[PDB]
Amino acid sequence: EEIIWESLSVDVGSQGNPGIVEYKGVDTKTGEVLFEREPIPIGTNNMGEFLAIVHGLRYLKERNSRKPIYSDSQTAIKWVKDKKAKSTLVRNEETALIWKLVDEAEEWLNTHTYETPILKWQTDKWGEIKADYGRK
RNA sequence: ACAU
DNA sequence: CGATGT
Ligand SMILES: [K+]
Ligand SMILES: [K+]
Ligand SMILES: [K+]
Ligand SMILES: [Mg+2]
Ligand SMILES: [Mg+2]
């Protein structure tokens, strides 16, 4: 089982969990940063990992790319498969922004199609995903 | 347990 | 050490 180097890798970064959430997507081979989301003041790790995959799907579809997406998040991969983000984060004025983005990402999944393979990055074999923030 |  | 999730 080898890395598919022609791929997009995504990852979340946070200050606290729940806390400030951001994410980015990079070229798996070169590490070139392809997109970065502006920090969201309160969210969870798994909400951010979900948003990152969905953004990757939208980014690749816009560019007519058949590349797969790597994520290290078992949870977010399943949420994308199900088209449903099963977060426990409370809904209040401070979490409204992240919940709006998650709701909108789900809505995009339910109104669009894609063949993009969403693959588990095997951290135990390969080390940290190329999109990692280096904060742990 | 596993993945973050 | 704590949190988010299956
Ligand atoms: K990190
Ligand atoms: K990891
Ligand atoms: K746990
Ligand atoms: Mg991750
Ligand atoms: Mg990471």
Image (cartoon, coloured by chain):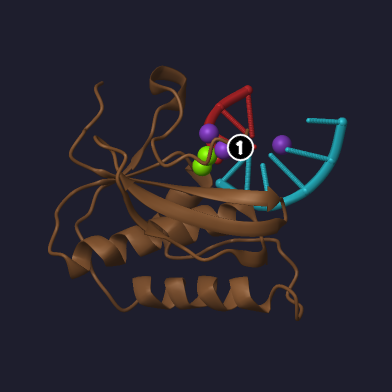
Chain colours: A brown, B red, C cyan
Question: Dot 1: few (<14), some (14–19), or many (≥20) neighbours within 10 Å?
Answer: few
Residue A63: image quadrant is bottom left
In the image, residue A58 above or below residue A23: below
In the image: residue A76, left or right of residue A66: right
Q: How many marks?
A: 1
Query: A7 and A76: which one is in front?
Result: A7
Residue A78 appears in the figure? no
Q: Residue at x 39, y 56 (%)?
A: A53
Q: Residue at x 42, y 34 (%)?
A: A129
Query: A76 and A18: which one is in front?
Result: A18
Which chain is home to disc 1? A
The percent position of residue A98, horizontal first and vertical second, equals 60, 71
In the image: residue A126, left or right of residue A100: left
Q: Is mark 1 within 8 Å of ligand 1?
A: yes
Quadrant the N terminus of chain A occupies: top left
Residue A62: image quadrant is bottom left
Q: Residue at x 43, y 49 (%)?
A: A77
Residue A120: image quadrant is top left
The percent position of residue A56, horizontal first and vertical second, equals 33, 58
In the image: residue A78, left or right of residue A68: right
Residue A6 appears in the figure? yes
Residue topped by disc 1? A135
Quadrant the C terminus of chain A occupies: top right
Looking at the rendered structure, the kind of residue marked 1 is Arg
In the image, residue A73 above or below residue A108: above
The percent position of residue A2, horizontal first and vertical second, equals 24, 22
The percent position of residue A58, horizontal first and vertical second, equals 29, 67
In the image, residue A121 above or below residue A90: above
Q: Residue at x 49, y 51 (%)?
A: A76
